[PDB]
Image (cartoon, rainbow over all chains, first blue to last red; front, side, top):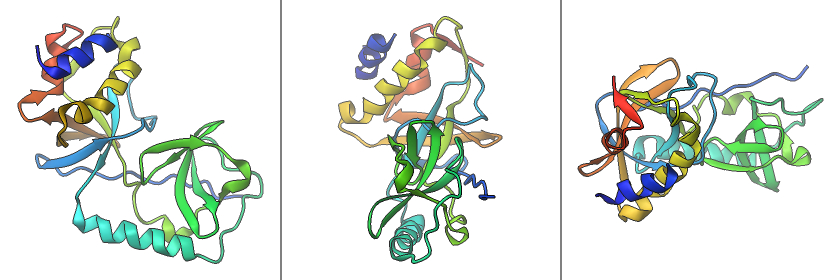
Length: 12
Length: 200
């Protein structure tokens, strides 16, 4: 799970 | 009556890697409801740097800044003067907000600090670029998340401690269709991986 994954996960 | 001015926006070079900052969202009538749009500011572009810097020097020194008979109409362009010899180009994107089109920053609308944009300063496009994330069909349930996704994307470069890069894949009206990426981390790939959208 990349860094950007984590960012996008919170937005969603 | 006052002339209604609408600057075009900067084009990104087709299939050419550029360095970009994700800035505040500048809305455009050219974005479909289901297109994930975003605003990029290309950085480290020396060709245009001297032109924009020269424009701002002349704007700050400009003598004949004239006010609006009425006021800056929503969706259209003028200048914002926060102090003597401090003049920047703005778009009134809403009733209470101006957009600094050459910096990518939203600020509060101040009626008294807004003046008309002289013709001589209407030749440069907005430094910011109107963009849309290319190659995607979004799940309808996800479309309400576009604002949240834009906030995340605005901080992505900071969290990567790296400059984000972009590449224009095509153009749809006034919109640059782009890929946004940091090394091998590609935005469309990471979104598609979350099942909120699919490739075209």
